[PDB]
Amino acid sequence: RLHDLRALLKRICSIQNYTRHVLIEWDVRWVNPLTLASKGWEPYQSASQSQVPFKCCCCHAIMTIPLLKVADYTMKLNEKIWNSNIIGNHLQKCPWRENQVDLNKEYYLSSQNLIREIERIHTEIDRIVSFHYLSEKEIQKLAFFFDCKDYSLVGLLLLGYTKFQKDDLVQCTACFHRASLKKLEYTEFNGHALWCRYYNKELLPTMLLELIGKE
Ligand SMILES: [Zn+2]
Ligand SMILES: [Zn+2]
């Protein structure tokens, strides 16, 4: 399937993985791991200090993202790259040229896919039994809805994270940034990319609370 969520997520994850040893100036609209993945692009080879190559999973066509050490022309350049490379480099009849994953429907939060977040949180809690930024009033209700006594775990999962290593590392499920639990203890620090589903921390808990009020 072209719009399969799991394939999109794995493309995003691989892009983030091979980009870790490099700093890239993404933008929320034109060029970012999300838009690349939504257009079927996967990492092709290891990126040099100057350019990051990608290959289409159907075409096998190659595109490249430049690197510079910047803010003056990022917008115009990235819009050009989106039109000419992320779309253009596709072969004429490749499905990814004229089609794109519906990110609003499948990736970003909506009332029709909030249940997936509920499932994720419940599954994480079950696998465990097997971060305060909301009012005590609110976290009480959120923890109650998930039948969980550990408020901090509920908050952490509401931030979209999941444990990564035996170490203090924790990884986001939608943008795959890595943060230390020590960082998130008593800090406003937002570890998400600007384009992440969870970048606005209050969005998911707010939708969940509004859902609670309607039951
Ligand atoms: Zn293609
Ligand atoms: Zn994230």
Image (cartoon, rainbow, N blue to C red):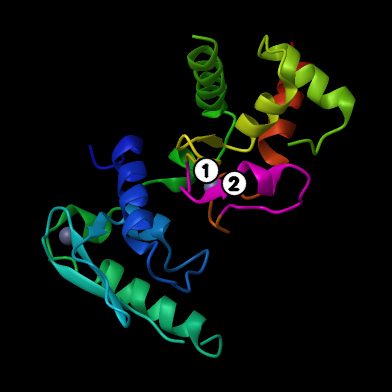
- Point out the residue furthest to the front here: 167
Mark 1 neighbour class, 10 Å CA radius: few under 14, some 14 to 19, many 20 or more = some
Residue 56, picture quadrant: bottom left
Percent position (x, y) of residue 197?
Answer: 55, 45
Picture quadrant of ligand 1 = bottom left
> Which kind of residue does numbered mark 2 sit on?
Ser
Q: Determine which residue is flagged by label 2.
A: 180
> Which kind of residue does numbered mark 1 sit on?
Leu
Query: Looking at the image, which is closer to me, 8 or 137?
Result: 137
Query: Looking at the image, which is closer to me, 104 or 126?
Result: 126
User: Which element carries disc 1, helix, strand or loop?
Assistant: strand
Rendered residue at 43%/77% (across/down):
78
Q: Is residue 214 visible?
A: no
Residue 140, picture quadrant: top right
Q: Which residues are magenta?
A: 174-192
Percent position (x, y) of residue 17?
Answer: 35, 54
Q: Is residue 177 found inside the magenta-colored segment of the image?
A: yes
Counting residues from the start of the chain, the first of labels 2 and 1 encountered is: 1
Residue 101 is left or right of residue 172, and the answer is: left
Task: Name the image quarter holding the C terminus.
Answer: top right
Percent position (x, y) of residue 143?
Answer: 73, 18
Where is 215 relative to 48, above or below? above
Residue 213 is left or right of residue 63, and the answer is: right
Whether label 2 touches label 1, CB < 8 Å: yes
Residue 208, picture quadrant: top right
Give the main secondary structure of the magenta stretch: loop
Residue 170 is left or right of residue 5, and the answer is: right
Q: Determine which residue is flagged by label 1.
A: 169
